[PDB]
Length: 145
Ligand SMILES: *[C@@H]1O[C@H](CO)[C@@H](O[C@@H]2O[C@H](CO)[C@@H](O)[C@H](O)[C@H]2NC(C)=O)[C@H](O)[C@H]1NC(C)=O
Ligand SMILES: *[C@@H]1O[C@H](CO)[C@@H](O)[C@H](O)[C@H]1NC(C)=O
Ligand SMILES: *[C@@H]1O[C@H](CO)[C@@H](O)[C@H](O)[C@H]1NC(C)=O
Image (tube, rainbow, N blue to C red; front, side, top):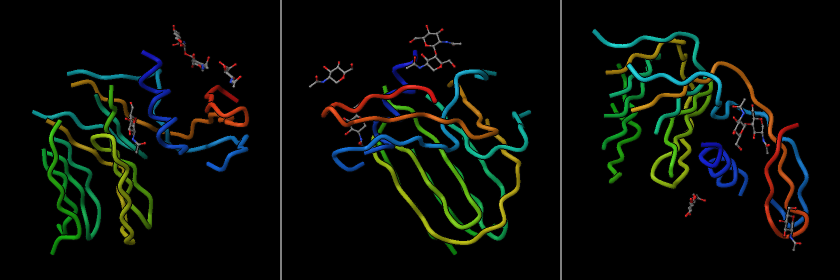
C-alpha cells in the first residue's frame, strides 16, 4: 500500500513552481508495522497509524476523536471526525500533527522522552528517511534518493 506513503508525502510537500529537492524527515516508513496491559515502545521520534500517550515534561500529548496537549493548563484541544494516514511528530521546540487531511503545528519548548504507550495498525519512526520530490513539469512526482 505504497500509495498511502505517497499521498502523505504529496500533502507534506505542498513547494514553488520549479522544485527539485530532497526532503529528510521522520517520515512514515514501510519496514516495521505493528498490530497487537498496554503496548510500550521506546526511542520514537514520530508515530503514525491508519488511545496513544507520548510522555514529556512539563507537557505531554495524547490522542483518544480528541487530541490534546496539556501539562502533566492546556495548549491544544481539538476534536475531529474520522486513504489518510494520521500521526504525531515531535521536536524539542514544536509539535506537528497530521489529522483528517490537515496539518497542524504548535510551538513550545518541552523535554520529550522516548516513551510512548498505547491501548489499528501502527507505524513507529526511529530515524530519518529521505524522499525526493520534483514538480518541475507541473505534476508533483515522488521517488527515493
Ligand atoms: C522507494 O523504496 C520502497 C522500498 O523501501 C519501495 O516500496 C515498494 O513499493 C511497491 C509498490 O509500489 C511494493 O510492491 C514493494 O513491495 C515495496 N518494496 C518493499 C521493500 O516493501 C518504493 O516503491 C520506492 N519508491 C518508488 C517511487 O519506487
Ligand atoms: C491530503 O490529501 C487528500 C487526497 O488524498 C486531499 O484531498 C487533501 O486536501 C490533502 N490535504 C492537504 C493539507 O493537502
Ligand atoms: C510529468 O512527469 C510524469 C512522470 O513521468 C508524467 O506522468 C506526466 O504526464 C508529466 N507531465 C507532463 C505535462 O508531461
